[PDB]
Image: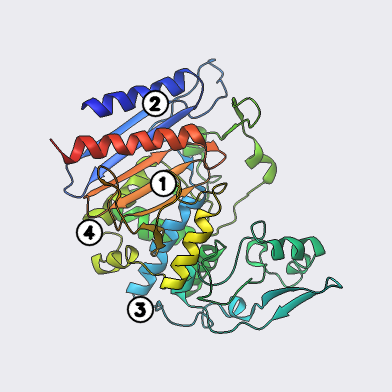
């Protein structure tokens, strides 16, 4: 290895030895196809097995991707566009007439009555994939917070509407960037345009081309990869020690396919998606279509307010290991760096990035010719030693690779 990489590798092993992280999978690939950096550290749980050992994280270990699923669903959405089933600026009301019928929540009275209102303008597939449709996640928006407390989402059952699709919009399309259930809608777009449930689409149109056999929504129907699945671990906010996280169990996710989250896979298979997109090999997506994913999709006003929002909310930190304050846009699939994160030393301008709940982070850097993947199974998102370790990971392999 190189000097910076052996120091980073030691930084990781000390975090496993000193109980800071349970484990991590770390992977980096070149566009030229001759960088194959993949290391594994520590365990896939904090729970000791029947053997009284910690079973190790490994490159094929099935892992909860959480919101890192959104990238996969962006590909499925764009795959449908390539095939002339949809168009980016086609109104969604053909394939999503239930979304298109939803109103926008304007606010409340002094009496406390909810003011619903007809949407101004039409929602498009491009809006969904850039989080500019105008819908938010309930627990983020103060209007949706109260709307939920009033109990108006309880009637979704009656009309057969799915819980995650139930909330009304908080704004019009093209007004704001707002993080929401857009890929859950995009997933529905894909299903009804193609006539297949997401899971069969994923298998046929993403796993098969790349030779993947450990990527699925239905983890319960795969006993072989369920037997060696990673566990979730949570970091205590009090003492900073890590404990077993059994929150998934009590939630009962339970065989329900949606495009925003839900997919389990090995880190190796997820890097295979990042790798294909980087080298323009056409197995998932037409190179011209990939070019679009890295194009700033946001209008100047929208990107200005998206930066304001992200810069003003460090407790969420969408741009994980990147500088807390940084000029970004959004392409189709993730956040785009509108500038070099640190001259030639780190991610270059035009690089695409998004992450996942258990501190999963991916990035693709066309201009630098690199793509990296930092894979953890540790909550909450925006964890400091995960963020820090990832930061030292990227810096190290960018350094080794590009000069000398």
> Dot 4 corresponds to which residue?
280
* Dot 3 crowding, Cα within 10 Å, few <14, some 14–19, many 20+: few
The image shows residue 201, relative to residue 133, as above or below, that is: above
> Dot 3 corresponds to which residue?
84
* Element on which disc 4 rests: loop
Pointers 1 and 3 in contact (CB under 8 A)? no
Tell me which label, 3 or 4, sits earlier in the chain. 3
Tell me which label, 1 or 3, sits earlier in the chain. 3
**Does residue 382 appear in this view?**
yes
Q: Position of residue 137 (x, y in %)?
A: 62, 60
Q: Is residue 107 left or right of residue 311?
A: right
Tell me which label, 4 or 2, sits earlier in the chain. 2
> Dot 2 corresponds to which residue?
12
- Place residue 180 in its image quadrant: bottom right
* Element on which disc 1 rests: loop
Q: Residue furthest left?
A: 404
> Dot 1 corresponds to which residue?
323
Q: Which-is-in-front pick, marks 2 and 1? A: 1
The image shows residue 320, relative to residue 76, as above or below, that is: above
Q: Which-is-in-front pick, marks 2 and 3? A: 2
Tell me which label, 2 or 3, sits earlier in the chain. 2
Pointers 3 and 4 in contact (CB under 8 A)? no
Q: Which-is-in-front pick, marks 1 and 3? A: 1
Distance (Cα) linking label 3 and label 4? 21 Å
| Marker disc for residue 198 | none
């Amino acid at each position: 290895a190189a000097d910076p990489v052996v120091l980073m590798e030691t930084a990781f092993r000390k975090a496993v030895k000193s109980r800071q992280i349970p484990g991590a999978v770390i992977m980096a690939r070149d566009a030229s196809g001759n960088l194959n950096y993949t290391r594994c550290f520590g365990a896939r749980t904090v729970r000791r097995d029947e053997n009284n050992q910690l079973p190790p994280l490994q490159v094929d270990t099935p892992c909860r991707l959480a919101s890192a699923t959104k990238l996969l669903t962006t590909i499925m959405a764009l795959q449908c566009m390539e095939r002339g089933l949809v168009d980016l600026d086609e109104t969604v009301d053909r394939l999503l007439p239930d979304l298109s019928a939803m109103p926008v929540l304007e606010g409340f009275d002094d009496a406390g009555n909810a003011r619903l209102r007809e949407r101004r303008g039409k929602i498009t597939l491009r809006h969904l994939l850039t989080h500019t449709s105008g819908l938010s996640y309930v627990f983020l928006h103060p209007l949706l917070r109260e709307y939920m407390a009033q109990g108006h989402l309880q009637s979704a059952e009656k009309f057969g509407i799915q819980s995650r699709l139930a909330p009304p919009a908080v704004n019009d399309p093209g007004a704001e960037w707002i993080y929401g259930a857009n890929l859950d809608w995009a997933g529905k777009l894909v299903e009804r345009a193609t006539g297949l449930d997401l899971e069969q689409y994923l298998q046929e149109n993403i796993c098969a081309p790349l030779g993947i056999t450990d990527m699925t929504f239905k983890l319960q129907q795969r006993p072989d990869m369920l037997a060696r699945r990673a566990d979730q671990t949570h970091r205590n906010s009090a003492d900073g020690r890590l404990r077993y996280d059994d929150s998934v169990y009590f939630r009962a996710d339970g065989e329900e396919c949606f495009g925003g989250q839900g997919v389990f896979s090995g880190p190796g298979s997820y890097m295979k998606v990042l790798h294909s997109l980087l080298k323009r090999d056409g197995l998932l997506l037409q190179p011209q279509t990939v070019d679009l994913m890295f194009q700033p999709a946001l209008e100047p006003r929208l990107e200005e307010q998206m930066n304001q929002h992200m810069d003003a909310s460090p407790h969420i930190n969408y741009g994980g290991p990147m500088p807390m304050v940084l000029r970004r846009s959004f392409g189709l699939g993730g956040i785009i760096a509108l500038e070099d994160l640190d001259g030639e030393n780190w991610r270059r301008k035009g690089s695409l990035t998004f992450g996942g709940g258990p501190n999963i982070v991916w990035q693709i850097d066309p201009k630098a010719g690199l793509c990296t993947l930092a894979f953890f199974q540790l909550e909450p998102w925006n964890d400091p030693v995960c963020r820090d370790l990832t930061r030292t990971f990227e810096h190290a392999i960018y350094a080794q690779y590009q000069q000398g």
